[PDB]
Length: 55
Length: 143
Image 1 (cartoon, chains in turn cyan, purple):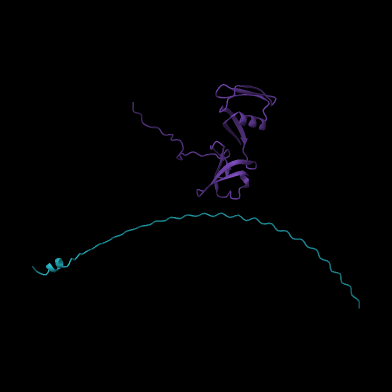
Image 2 (cartoon, rainbow over the protein chains, first blue to last red):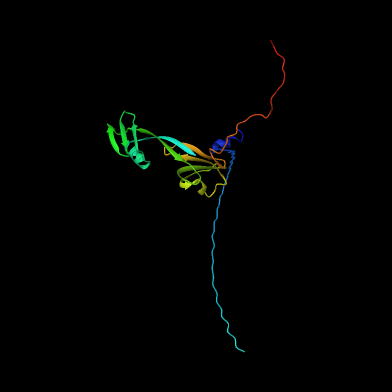
């Protein structure tokens, strides 16, 4: 009797669910760098200029 | 600085080492009783030297910042380890952060030669003690 009978009359499937997730990620990064530059320079030059005048 | 290392060499390795580091006259023995004799840097006598016979030989290596090293290992302050071949200790580009240097001894052994900016012989390795003078106090006796 009652209304609930209709649920059985037409096959009714009630489905539920619940997913509860948790996630913690911890990352530690360290880095070191070492550089070294060594240069050398050398330049040499020569010039000549001759001026002759008449007046 | 002189580093002494004991090694075990077969006959071929022993002959190569002896002729490379000149030996005039001396007898090398092995585990199984076999021996070889060098006399005036010549192999005069050998006595039943089978394979897998190990001759124990001590070797002296002079270590100096100027002299190049065959194979050494360096550790910085942060923790990075590196290895170098055929490079003098002074030659390293970054000696500022180099904390330790060991010498890899071809046996995978490690011998410390450089510690905190100095050769290992120059370093003094201070111990620990609380600072205090003599007690010089008279105590009661329980007798």
